[PDB]
Image (tube, coloured by chain):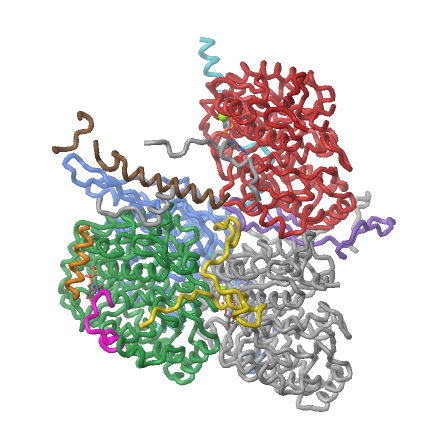
Chain colours: A green, B orange, C blue, D brown, G yellow, I red, J purple, K cyan
Amino acid sequence: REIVSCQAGQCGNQIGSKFWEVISDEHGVDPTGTYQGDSDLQLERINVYFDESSGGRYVPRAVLMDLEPGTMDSVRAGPYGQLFRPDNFIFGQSGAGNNWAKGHYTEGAELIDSVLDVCRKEAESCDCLQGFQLSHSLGGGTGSGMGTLLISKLREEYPDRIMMTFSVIPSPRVSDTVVEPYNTTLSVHQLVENSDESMCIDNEALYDICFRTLKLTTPTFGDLNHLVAAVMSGVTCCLRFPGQLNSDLRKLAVNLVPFPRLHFFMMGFAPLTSRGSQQYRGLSVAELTQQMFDAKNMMQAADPRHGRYLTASALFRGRMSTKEVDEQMLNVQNKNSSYFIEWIPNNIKSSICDIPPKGLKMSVTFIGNNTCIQEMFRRVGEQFTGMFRRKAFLHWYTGEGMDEMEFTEAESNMNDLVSEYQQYQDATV
Amino acid sequence: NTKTKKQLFMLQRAE
Amino acid sequence: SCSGRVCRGCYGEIAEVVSHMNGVYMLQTKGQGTAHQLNAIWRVLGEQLEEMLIKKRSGIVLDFLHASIKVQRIKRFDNSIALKLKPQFVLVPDFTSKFHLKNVLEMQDAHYHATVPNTVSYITIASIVGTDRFVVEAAVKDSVREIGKYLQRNAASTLTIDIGVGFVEFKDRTYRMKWSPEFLARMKASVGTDGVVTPYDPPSRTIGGPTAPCRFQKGCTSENLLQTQVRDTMLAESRLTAAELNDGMGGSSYRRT
Amino acid sequence: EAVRAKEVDTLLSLQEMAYQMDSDFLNEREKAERYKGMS
Amino acid sequence: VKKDYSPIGTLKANSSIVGRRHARKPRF
Amino acid sequence: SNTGGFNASQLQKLREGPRFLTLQTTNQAIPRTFDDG
Amino acid sequence: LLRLAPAYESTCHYQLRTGRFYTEDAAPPHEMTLPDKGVTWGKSRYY
Amino acid sequence: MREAICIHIGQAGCQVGNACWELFCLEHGIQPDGSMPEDDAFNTFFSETGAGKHVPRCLFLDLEPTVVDEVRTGTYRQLFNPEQLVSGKEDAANNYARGHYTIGKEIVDLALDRIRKLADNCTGLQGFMVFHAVGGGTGSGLGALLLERLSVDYGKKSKLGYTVYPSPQVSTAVVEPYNCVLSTHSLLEHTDVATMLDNEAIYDLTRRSLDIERPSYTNVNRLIGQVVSSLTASLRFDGALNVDLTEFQTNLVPYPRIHFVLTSYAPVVSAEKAYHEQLSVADITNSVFEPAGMLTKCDPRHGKYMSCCLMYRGDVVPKDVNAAIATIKTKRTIQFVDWCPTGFKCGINYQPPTVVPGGDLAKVQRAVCMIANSTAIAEVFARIDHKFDLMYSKRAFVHWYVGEGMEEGEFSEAREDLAALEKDYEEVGAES
Amino acid sequence: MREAICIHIGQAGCQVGNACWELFCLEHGIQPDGSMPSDAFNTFFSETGAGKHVPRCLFLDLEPTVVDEVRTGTYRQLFNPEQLVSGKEDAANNYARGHYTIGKEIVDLALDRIRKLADNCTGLQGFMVFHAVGGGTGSGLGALLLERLSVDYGKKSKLGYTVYPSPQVSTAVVEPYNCVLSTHSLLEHTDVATMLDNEAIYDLTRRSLDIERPSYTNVNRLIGQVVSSLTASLRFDGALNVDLTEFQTNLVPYPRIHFVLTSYAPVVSAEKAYHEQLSVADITNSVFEPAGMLTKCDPRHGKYMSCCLMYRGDVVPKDVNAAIATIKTKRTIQFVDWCPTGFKCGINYQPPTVVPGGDLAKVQRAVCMIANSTAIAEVFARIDHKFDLMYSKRAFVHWYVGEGMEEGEFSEAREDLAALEKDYEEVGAES
Amino acid sequence: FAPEELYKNCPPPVLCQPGYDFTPISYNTFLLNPQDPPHGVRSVQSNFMHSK
Amino acid sequence: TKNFVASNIVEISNMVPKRRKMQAPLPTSRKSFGETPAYIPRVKREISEEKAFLESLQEA
Ligand SMILES: Nc1nc2c(ncn2[C@@H]2O[C@H](COP(=O)(O)OP(=O)(O)OP(=O)(O)O)[C@@H](O)[C@H]2O)c(=O)[nH]1
Ligand SMILES: Nc1nc2c(ncn2[C@@H]2O[C@H](COP(=O)(O)OP(=O)(O)OP(=O)(O)O)[C@@H](O)[C@H]2O)c(=O)[nH]1
Ligand SMILES: Nc1nc2c(ncn2[C@@H]2O[C@H](COP(=O)(O)OP(=O)(O)O)[C@@H](O)[C@H]2O)c(=O)[nH]1
Ligand SMILES: [Mg+2]
Ligand SMILES: [Mg+2]
Ligand SMILES: [Zn+2]
């Protein structure tokens, strides 16, 4: 089983670069490519994310896609840029300009042949493929458009293969764009039926975590990318290492997706400690369980207090014991039965991996299918309706083959997803 | 080593 | 003869079955849906797909088909773009897995230069018909499910589904796509002198081509016959429960499921 | 035997990449048929 | 214990075929 | 051009080990001996 | 702080290593290298 | 001769098998390499080769390579045959349909192939021991497929299914009720005796008796291996009342459907409190029927006991067994159904259970493992059925099973057959 | 006495003969120079007045690469220079070129060599022809040589070990034509034809021999093991000695039914060998497993006609009978109703020798299996469906037409294969 | 060679790709024929046999 | 507006399993198995036509 990574746009490419840095440190791979791992348990499943060259070097199984050479040049100039494959590097001269029409219809189509060639080549290089993992931002042009087109082609080429999608959904109070509601509305409807699960990243929640949970004076986009990459590694720690109670991405999808449209998930990591408060708190399974369900720990900005958890998944890493990795879940179920849905008993799945992430002897990643995720879809709904009632910023899209009908179709799908979540949130037996 | 020079300059800016 | 090679199958049979069932379309319409409305929805969906392919835009009907135009890039004298548009029809992998059919065209070949696929606009279909987009979506899901259902129920003779682009004829585990000459002529007219490749026309599985008088027009089947027959086949596929089911009103009696 | 075969194959691949990276064809070193530019 | 012989005296092979599942040409 | 040289383990193996890279035949490299063990 | 001690050993490895011995010191020291699954391990083994 | 083929399916089955085989090697004195340091009593579990090596009569199955690679890289790598240690390509992902229809179906033939190699290697086979968990995907689906294929392949050979059902309020997966209810078909039709080993009861037992604040799956599997070793010591070693697998299944199964049987072990006490107790036969027998002294989370007093089979080991004597049983009969808080006045089966072996070094069990002169068919077993089945009703009431997670290759009529039939089993427990527990 | 003449046609035949003669020399202690330091070899080796031991083999090939390599190889001093017959240019995957144009100008001297080998022999058992109908000279020249041997040497036994083309992998596109055309000779002028397609050997080496990179060398080593297991009966003393005639009369029920599968067990690696107790019953079960054969042919998709067992080593008829009884009691494999006996047995006291540097681990007992079964129609149906898809509109037929056969030979081969299919279908019928 | 004459009393050989990288062939199972001793012969046994 | 819950009810209850893998037809089960293929008479037809053409040129 292998997860081949695809990363699109500036946000997606930088997130993928930080992810590959984290994975290389976990598996002992240096920036150059050698293996300095203390134990070869790291190497025994290194094929999941790394392809071995005949010289013993390890190359990430990654596809760097963008419409601007600048992001590719920066990521290859980074400390771990030398690790990636130049053939895997793919870029276009003319950027999307935060336009889904450029990202999907005009400039995406010309370069999608090359990205499909590279992705397929890596696919048959895989002896057995678990699936694809695409990281991107829905607020941009190249991240949203070409990312959605890649997802649409990849799902239909490999129907039974997992399609992880890590989409950074933009927010009003951190937004640095005026057409990001258009891009998100035009992209996430494709994510609805083209990806088997799309956990959502929010920059405002990441900044809130860095401000309070991490107490970081000067975190950056790289710090937010590392926040995402921690969970991106914890989600497949079970694939990459043996564990007491192992799982895989299909197991997580089966346990977290009750209905096909309900695959947009929560986002959390634990423990998240500041430099000063590291020694002042006792890290253990109990505090991990309490911090994973903490709303302020959540790296998606939609507090669960207004929603209900369809399902939850806790991927713990480190030497542990099962009764307490599970009775904490049972206790939180009992004490938050109001916040957990009644008609689906035992909402929480627990997975155990014996190898903790670098820097800890104990960690956990939380992925929840809470019904509060409808909040950001709602907000982008009002933003989209506000800009679409006057047809503002629509000529940019519609001069390039796009027209009015699919904008209304995207709003239609937004209402469909919102009602799909709301009806199951308030449904009774 | 232009990449290395870029890394060093980014480190100085970060500092 | 009514023994095959003649009895063409219209979409009206699928519409009648969808209307006479406890399916999604009936739930959405609260039992007010009709086979006539199903036929109207299917016809306008075919028209919308035909318009989408006219617009050099590949159209995907969910879980049923992905009709796409393969484009070939040839540089003219002054290096202006000249297009060779080759229509191509491949079923959705979901449908192929659902009903164990095989596509003549492999999928990477299909999407190497297929244009960007978009969903058929259910809202436009509903606007043309006169109903709700939710009704249209329920109707199309039920229709495609029963279209695939027909073969697994019983599969030798043709089932010809009409689409604006062309007719798809279903055999046991095999299908055959016949692009309609009207749609091909419209592509040639609206291509803007770029050039349209006439796709391979396999020999028609029914005498007279896909545009042949089907069982309805010939008189082989009627609405009453279809109703009685669908009741009979539902009874045949139904299976008994192992033990008495308490049921309401204290009726432990078994029940076919 | 398997370990020795893997080692010799890997070494022969190392010589492979060394020759390919040092080759005049790939590195554009040295002219009617091979004129490149002014020195 | 089920060993049926033809009148000529030849052992016929036993069968476990329940019946003919009529895979036919479609009609409702 | 500015991609990076060999990997460090690659240097190690190259040091541990225009000319033809391999110049032996199949039924000359096939094993026909038993080791001391 | 102090660098974390290198410990990559599964619960099942600990079980099999200390299942025959009363105390860890009597048990063989944990070795980072794991023994080869077969003489020539490949993907053909996995079905 | 006089052997029994061990099959381990899935995650839980594989760790249970690892614990079981380390315990068996400890019993019979085989080093992890596979060699020795009338000792042929190992023949029931280890096939002996002319070299003197003893290969276990075991078969590991798991759709995910990690667990079997763990086994192949563990201490007992040279103990196990390279074959009969099958590795899957990708896991069943907690999906019964995935393990039974579309992925388990194309390796069940290799499963039967290696099982048949074991069968032809062996000569006096008494049956199969299928260790798995119905909560998961592989252990449910592929386990059901393997059991039902073995049913037609080997006829009326005994198939003891040691199964880890989902526990009442301790849970691991959300599709656990689905997988359990679906696998109950095969565990009901193609299994003579099924033994519950849910994790909750073992957890409470470890917490309250073994005085271990942090036990894990390692200790749970140690306990399960101790239970299976105690059960099969009658055929492993010499004893007062030698009982075979079929010998006790015929007495534990009153009706073809009525065969799920709870289990318990005694004395399970840590070494810190083990020397503080008169670990007599009467004491251990009384501790067996303790609701918290068993390995199944169901109160036995909430139903009519139907048949208890006791496996005594060590210096235990038949009259202390009989006095304990007479006291149990007098203690009518646990009552037998009216049509089974006997209700007891006794099997005494002279070999005390050898503790696993580094384990949590204490060395005891005598031990007892009891397996009971009782109508109180309906509690856990009804709880799982109600969870299934809540989940299936509006088709949650059914799309996974259907898109992976199973009908909805199968779900409905599973619920209906489980309701029939619910009614049957109460029918047979009714007074005459 | 009891001599046997080996003939190797084509590249496949030449390499198979290389492996076979390596193994034979290893068994008989004959060094590559051709002398034993310190007379079962008389079957395959002939004494010379100078003390050399010349093999009774003819390496006939139409192109010089393989024969030249054999000449320049380790067994240069072993192989008689005249016994290595090499043409100038190959048939180039053309049955026509190997049967009508180039095959004729070398077949005369091939028969001359065969005569010079046979006149030395006194008790010649028969001929062992190793070839492959996939190629041109392996099919065409092989067919010509078989016809010329049948027309003059009489009713001598002829074991044609043929590497038939594989069900789904092709190293050539015209091999369906080649095999279909050569099946004429391999149906009328071969005493017993042995299926040896490569994919079954590849699967055997993948799953049992435990090698991630098998090659032609390993395939030929396994083929040589099978050949030695079959022919050791007429060389070494054994409990039950059977000859080529002895088992052809048992494996040929009808004149048109002489195609047979091979299997060999145990065929295991060194790691797996000591992990198992290889008994007679165990090895017999591994033999009768449909997975353990050297043909991609499924007996469970057919019925058994006859099976011949070559036991080697410390095997005893004691356990041979028990294994046969267990196999008969097994239900998955079915024998045809008109052959209740269906079994032929032969035991040898000589265990199979292991080639140095090989992948087979030494086993105290082994057994090979040569079987005629109704399942042969499976591989014939596959291969001529390949042929029919090929010949629907006459692709790659101008080559054959221009290389000197009438195109009606393709048709005649088609009806010949149709008749072979039909009688394969209807001789397994219940009476 | 049709399945419903070839498999009158035996399960079909369900083809399965895993275990092979090429076309699947089959796998034998342990199923035994019913006891059909030849009439009148003594219960002749060479070695220990699995009792039907 | 729809009741998404009830829509999922009927959708899931009505859709049938997919991803099931059945067997390829047996090669011996081919329709032309055992007898001459239908196109072989056609092949002999053009063979006879070509031979007749050559014979006609010779006769001329
Ligand atoms: N007693 C015990 N039970 C275990 C162990 N590991 C897993 N389980 C059981 O397995 C259940 C979860 O199922 P899975 O994680 O899918 O494991 P599985 O049942 O083997 O199914 P697969 O993972 O698909 O092979 C839990 O409820 C546990 O009861 C173990 O080591 N000991
Ligand atoms: N088992 C085995 N088969 C071989 C070997 N070499 C070639 N073959 C067979 O030869 C077939 C291909 O035919 P060719 O390439 O024409 O070789 P050929 O049959 O000897 O015929 P020529 O090349 O004309 O000499 C393949 O299908 C193989 O089965 C070998 O070394 N071992
Ligand atoms: N977490 C994170 N967010 C980023 C990063 N870079 C950009 N973003 C977010 O992405 C939004 C702009 O997206 P954009 O870069 O135009 O997407 P693109 O067109 O696909 O490259 C901004 O609002 C940022 O908040 C990054 O490195 N990390
Ligand atoms: Mg698992
Ligand atoms: Mg050649
Ligand atoms: Zn009609």
When asked about the image quadrant of residue A147, the answer is bottom left
Count of numbered circles on the image: 0
- Residue A221 highlighted magenta (yes or no): yes
Compared across the picture, whether E3 is left or right of A429 comes to right
Compared across the picture, whether I30 is left or right of K11 comes to right
Whether residue C128 is visible to the viewer of this picture, yes or no, is no
Whether residue I378 is visible to the viewer of this picture, yes or no, is yes
Where is residue D2 shown, x and y percent of the image?
49, 45
Q: Nearer the viewer, residue C189 or I405?
A: I405
For image coordinates 82% across by 43% down, the residue present is E8
For image coordinates 66% across by 27% down, the residue present is I36
**Image quadrant occupied by the C terminus of chain I:** top right
Where is residue A82 shown, x and y percent of the image?
27, 52
- Residue A7 highlighted magenta (yes or no): no
Examine the rendered structure and indicate whether residue I118 appears above or below residue E21.
above
Compared across the picture, whether C127 is left or right of I103 comes to left
For image coordinates 35% across by 42% down, the residue present is D14
Where is residue C91 shown, x and y percent of the image?
38, 51
Q: Which of A290 and I417 is in front in this view?
A: A290
**Image quadrant occupied by the N terminus of chain I:** top right
Compared across the picture, whether I87 is left or right of I297 comes to left
Q: Nearer the viewer, residue I176 or F1?
A: F1
Q: Which residues are drawn in magenta?
A: A208-223
Examine the rendered structure and indicate whether residue K54 appears above or below residue C34.
above
Examine the rendered structure and indicate whether residue C251 appears above or below residue C52.
below
Where is residue A120 shown, x and y percent of the image?
35, 49
